[PDB]
Structures are given as C-alpha cells and as structure tokens.
Length: 377
Image (tube, rainbow, N blue to C red):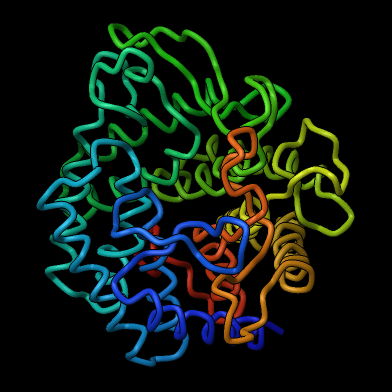
C-alpha cells in the first residue's frame, strides 16, 4: 500500500510550498527544516519534480502552479546564466522544464529545456571525449574530470536529440556513458565517484573520490547514480551492455544492504549503526531497480526479483525513515547524507532523496515514471 505514504508527502509538500514561497529546498542541517536557496545550486530541479509528481497524483492545481512558478525561475536562471557552468543542467532542467513538457505539453517549457540542453552541450570536451563535470573549461584540477552522477544529466541531452533530430546530442551522450562504463565502474561491480582524463587527448589518468570515504571505496549514492543512470541511458540508447552494467551494480548494492534495509553512506566503512546512512542512495536505487525491471522481458525470472527488491526498499524507507506530516517536518525521509567527510549534512533531509522516494512511490502506485524520458518511450 503506497497511498498513505504518498499522502504524507502531499501534505508536507503543500505546506512547504506556502512556507518556501519562491525559494528552493536543498538539504536540512541538524533540524527538520530545509536550508533554502534562490535557485543557485544543483538540486533546485528536485523541488520542481516533487511539485509535478504531486500534481500528477492529485490533479490539484496548487501543486501545478507552484511548479510553473519554479519553471519561470529556471527561465530567468538560464537567461542570466547564474551558476550554470557545470554538468548539472540535466538534474535542474529535466525535472522542471522538461517535466512540464511531459506533463502538459507546454511549448515554452519545451523551448526552455532545449535551450538548457544546448547549454549543457557546452560542457562537452571534444579533445577528451567527455562532459566536464565541474569548473570552467580548462580548470587545472577538474578540466578533464567526470563523475558518475553525470549519467543522470545525459537524459536531458538524449531527449533533446529526439526532439530536434540533431544526432550530436546522442553522439555525445553515448560516448560519455560508454566512457563512464569503462572507467568509473570497477571489476568487482563497485564504482569510483570520479575519474580524471588528460584534457588534451582523453588519456585515462586515474579514478578518485570526492564524497566517498577513499579513492578506492564505494560511495553508495555514487553506486546508486550508476544503477539508475546506466539504466536510463540503456533505455535511450538500446544498449544491452549499459543495462548489464546497471544490473551488475544493482546486485552489488543489494548484497550490501543492512538489516533495516537502508544503506550506509559508503560500503567500505564499518557497516554498523555508528556510521552515517544515506537514505537518498536507497531511494535512488529503488527507482533504478524499477527502471531496470521495466526493460527486462516478462519471461526473465530476475525481473520480478528486481521489482520486489524495489518494493522492499521503499517499504524499508517508509517504515523506518519516512516523516509523517506532523505540520512541522519539511522532508519526506530522514538520514540522508550530503558530504560525510566534509561534515556537510551527514544525517539530514536531501531534496534529491525526497524526489526519488516520491518517484518510486508514483512508479509503484500509478506507473508514473518521472521526467527522464517521455511517457511511453
């Protein structure tokens, strides 16, 4: 049963919209209140996504109008190019502008998403064959660095390619996804957080972490980005190798889920209650598991196993981590972690965790698949 779980999210969201106003939630910091920003981070799209999902579930225009207002903010953000010189254009615009196009076919929203996709293409580095994740072009430290999270920024490009017919979008996304599979994914099915290439020729330099415990550890959200990310790219590209990788990474993740069903922040640290968790990694994986299953043939016995693993994850989140709408709580699930070693919100709400938790509930209850691709594709 997912209706009551969704109900708490609907209540929390409706109240949040009236409190946040035109502001955007990011993460909490030691309390049940979200730290807010004026659309200046990489997570603003998750708020839009949540509003759109709530609208799709209820048909209640209070959610739609809030979403539309955030889209207007995104139109302004792009026109002013405020903090958009990085790869997170996908997370920001797929869940806001593209989402509105998916929900109600708004032409201006479609244009905004395409304008955004065009801006994201500026991050492509022809000489290295990758999308630069962080910093300005040529940045000494990150000029040739990619991160596994970027897999979720590719849908915006793939979608833009199918909308415009411009083969460049798919070419770049496919190349980046394949390069990610070869260098970000490890031989034991674990994964690196980031990887460095020579900006001049694309030679592989080394793998390295940013939010994981060590360069060779397994940041669980990173593993999660791989699971859902490779599955989303596999759908767009009809690439069986990417789907296989998503499955391998998923099995690796699942074999390391603790007794309460929600993962710790890194698989290579003490797997005991004293270690911080990352409910957001589990939420992302729940969506990834369902995505994987949707691409498997009905005759494949592992299909139902992936679906059940997803239901079990959502249940674990609902029962042990979900916030009830008590008129105060501003987040859907507790114990997410942003940057543990950096001491940044290690036991808090994360708006992305909230978005994926709700997307999983909508997938399970209504078959609503989010805003990574057109419905029916």
